[PDB]
Image 1: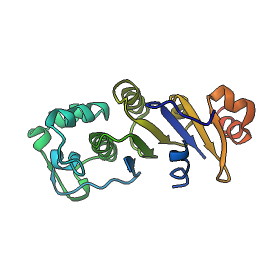
Image 2 (image 1 turned 180 degrees about the horizontal axis):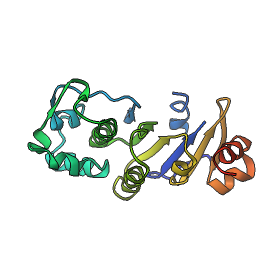
Image 3 (image 1 turned 60 degrees about the horizontal axis):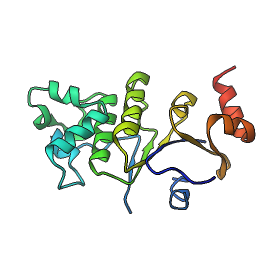
Length: 188
C-alpha cells in the first residue's frame, strides 16, 4: 500500500517530504539552486565522496546527461569551474549537481525541483537513466509538472500538507481530489 519498491522513481506533487521517507543517514538531496566552487569539474563532482573513481564520476555524469558536454571541453573533467559555476548555463549547473549527487551513491535521492533549467527531452533522458542504471537507489522527484509525474513509477500527492494520495495516475484519479485538480489544471 503505502510502501515503495526499492529502486523505483516516485514523483512528488503538492522539506515536508523528509518526514515520510523513513516511514516510507544516506539521503542525498539536490537543491533547486546549485553549489559549485572554484576548482575543476572533477573536484566538484567528487565533493562529499572522496573515494569516487574517475569512471564512477563518468558514469554519474552520463546518467545526468552532462558527460558529452564535459568531454567536449578542452580539459575535459579537469576543466575549470569558476566560483558559483558562473561559467556554465543554468541547465549545465543543474546537471552537474545531479551528477555530484549520483557520485555519492545514495540509497535515497531527492531531486528538489532541480530540473527547471533542463529541457524536457533531456529531463526524460535523465529520468530514464536513473531507472535503467541507478538501482540501489529510490528516487523522489519533487515536481510541478504532470508530464514529469507520469514518468515516475508512483506518484505521491501532498496537499495540506499531509499525504493526499499515493499510487499510479489511474489510482490517484480514483481517490485523490487534489490530484484530479492538478491534472485538470494542466489538461482539459
